[PDB]
Amino acid sequence: GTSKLKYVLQDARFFLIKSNNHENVSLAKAKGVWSTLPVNEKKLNLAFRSARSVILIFSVRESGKFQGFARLSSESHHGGSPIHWVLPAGMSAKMLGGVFKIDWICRRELPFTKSAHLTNPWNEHKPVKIGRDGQEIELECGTQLCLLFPPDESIDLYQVIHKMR
Ligand SMILES: CNC(=O)c1n[nH]c2c1CCC2
C-alpha cells in the first residue's frame, strides 16, 4: 500500500541531493547517513527543526536517474564514526559538515524519463530533475515525485512513523 508513505510525507519538506558518484549513495544506503557542504547543512538543520519530515531525494550526477529517498532522523552531528566518502579533486573530508542520520524510505531507482511531468516552483518551474545539490523541492512536486518511485517492499515505515514528533 501507499497509506503509511503518504502519512510520512504529509506536510514534509523535500531537498534534491546531487551525489558526484554512486559510491557515496552506496555508503549512505549501507550506513544510514549523509553529509553535505556547510551551506546545505545549515539549511537542512533549519528544516529538520521546522517540519514533521525532511526528505532527501538522491540523484547521482550523469546517471539520468534518482537512486531513492530518505528521511532525516537527526540534525547534523560531529564526532561519530568516520565515513570514507569519495570527495572531489582537491577537497578534504573536513570540508563537509556534520553527519545526518537518515532512514531510507525507498532504495529503488526512478529514471528521469518518468518525472518529466513534474516541475519545481522553487527552481523556476524547471523539471524536478534539474537543480543544484540542496535545491528545495516544493511540497506538491516533492510528494508526487516520491509517489512515482517503485514500491520498496523491504521497507517498514512503522518505525519511521514512531520517530515523528
Ligand atoms: C556525501 N556528501 C558528498 O559527496 C558531497 N556533498 N557536498 C559536496 C560533496 C562533494 C562535493 C561537494
Image (cartoon, rainbow, N blue to C red):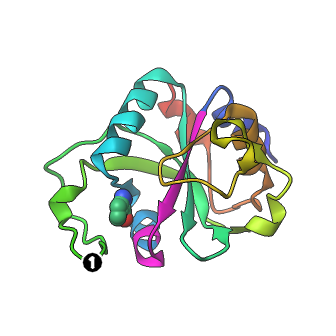
With 90 as the anchor, is 113 left or right in this view?
right
Q: Is residue 22 magenta?
A: yes
Residue 125 picture quarter: top right
Q: Is residue 121 magenta?
A: no
Task: Give percent across and percent down for residue 154.
Answer: 64, 62
- Residue 56 vs 113, above or below: the answer is above
Task: Give percent across and percent down for residue 85.
Answer: 30, 70
With 67 as the anchor, is 121 left or right in this view?
right
- Neighbor class of circle 1 (other Cα within 10 Å; few <14, some 14-19, many 20+) is few
Q: Nearer the viewer, residue 122 or 31?
A: 122
Going by the numbered disc 1, the residue's amino acid type is: Ala
Residue furthest right in the image? 117
Point 40% across, 35% down: residue: 43
Residue 45 picture quarter: top left
- Let me know if residue 45 appears in the view: yes
Label 1 CB sits under 8 Å from any ligand 1 atom: no
Point 80% across, 49% down: residue: 118
Point 13% across, 49% down: residue: 79
- Let me know if residue 105 appears in the view: no
Point 16% across, 58% down: residue: 94
Q: Nearer the viewer, residue 93 or 82?
A: 93
- Residue 20 vs 72, above or below: the answer is below
Circle 1 sits on which residue? Answer: 89
Find ligand 1 in the image and state its quadrant. bottom left
Magenta region: 13-25
